[PDB]
Image 1: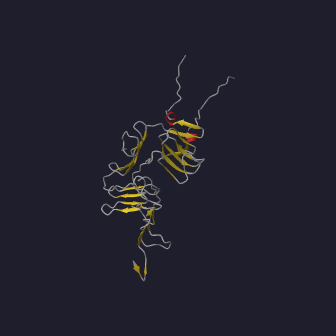
Image 2: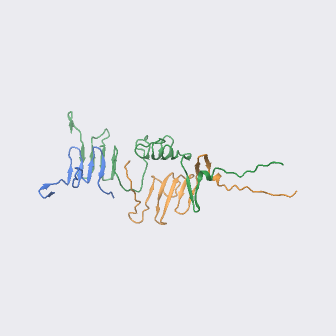
Image 3: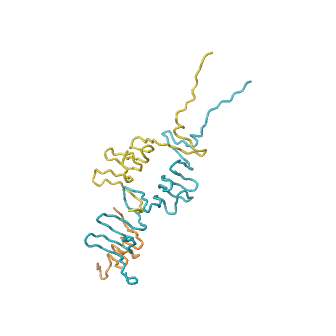
Length: 147
Length: 98
Length: 49
């Protein structure tokens, strides 16, 4: 599309290799959407919206060196009161951080101490025993009196 | 790629010999590298887990879940060390005649 | 593809924006496979393998 007096390429469909670029090229000559079928790389400078796709391997990648590579439901952050699942490595502390639950009941790991402000239940073949009650430190003590 | 959303995942063995597993780059099963490894080993047909590093790790080989890491479990009264909690501290008595 | 006496679009490759639709458009004007590179959305009314 011709702006001012210069033509800026908006897309380029290569006949020889099939490489496809979409959008206005940035200062580095890379389109916001780029296709490289020689290497088969889906590199887009944006967000992807879809529903269901299968996969095996995942890498939490820090693209710009400052973004936090983590998984979160929409509207869910680290340590917030919102209900959701948050799992990732905090770049400031270089520690994997976990946040599953809500404001009241949650399971959180900050990379150092795994604290759970939720009912932690562990099962046995004889049944289920409350972990909090199981380890309340109930000590059988004796008190003595002379009479 | 960097970020794509999804709901359903299948660890698929395409050629019948590749191990369908998830791993960070440079991370394998049982290695000393820090990372997360989760998948089913085709040789043993057992799901294998490897989260942590050479010293502190949480590993499951499909048979025994062993953790060479500080396992902490929380209670409303606070946090009690699981290793100290189950050290088998038995109140024993020794008797002497005098 | 012309069915009966009306042409129903099967694909549309937009030159200006690069938007690509694949398949027979439904009642809402959305193809079963739609590409929106302006928004970069992979929205398909089906399954992905």
